[PDB]
Length: 99
Image (cartoon, rainbow, N blue to C red; front, side, top):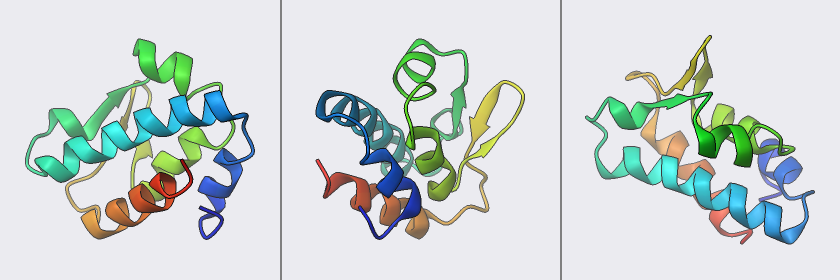
């Protein structure tokens, strides 16, 4: 948690909002860690219902995706093939220990 700036920001939310956002964040990370060779898992459409309603309006949520290794484009957030899965796992754990 507090060891990460983005996670520390995410922690400033109320309990229900934190749990909802963190659950979705762990879902995205786990999909990649479960199959690092699947490109669908490496892209999140910004207009997607879950993203636009559970992360976009939440303090620190999108910042956590950035620390994981995702980068923002015009329509999607993308986790590059060059990105470190070790860094991804690191942020994933720092979020999980705060739930």
